[PDB]
Length: 240
Ligand SMILES: CC(C)[C@H](NC(=O)C(F)(F)F)C(=O)N[C@@H](C)C(=O)Nc1ccc(C(F)(F)F)cc1
Ligand SMILES: [Ca+2]
Image (cartoon, rainbow, N blue to C red; front, side, top):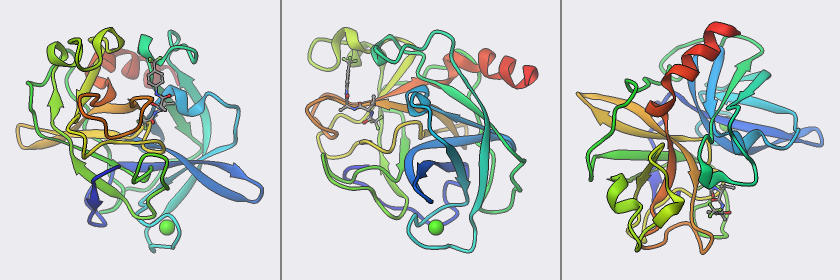
């Protein structure tokens, strides 16, 4: 997150760290939202290489034991059948990961509240992006969880000339674009939490930023609109 601030420890307890293996060690590659005690929602582009992944729940500082972390293997990845690696701008950037075991819930590990199908937020709706990705364009990973208030830019403004144009589809949520705050690499697959009737629910799965850098004026961060995928989500958990 560029222009963010650090988060409280138990602030966003459905945030996870999606890590892959490097040698004996593990590196954070993406975020994700715990949706079931054995299922994580993340972006499909995060599991496009055939890596060994793991999930870390209850995480706050990546480089230091917090006393709160649970670490579980990824047993099965079900990415969206229409996802195409060569074209994020087509949309469908979503994947579900079956964990090897059920994580234990406590005040650090909670399930993410998903929106109702079809739900579209109004322009300038209050949302927060969370993640351990780059703090500057071409910078480095945050070691503690960061957060920025990232208000939505609705579809009509996001797909106008001046912003993302045709690159953004209606199955996507835009948020930010002020030139100060954004999501950035390593935040991919993470949540956009938006307050809806006194409940923060996960309306976005971070998908992409501009090629000229993370915090770019009028290129808001682009998220997969979770509410366009509620039936496929539900139909995958009932299958597996
Ligand atoms: C999509 C992810 C690999 C990568 N995502 C992120 O950085 C994220 F964290 F914001 F989600 C990304 O946007 N990286 C930038 C550097 C990039 O490649 N952006 C990009 C934007 C649009 C398009 C296009 F037009 F094809 F859709 C292609 C690449
Ligand atoms: Ca830690």
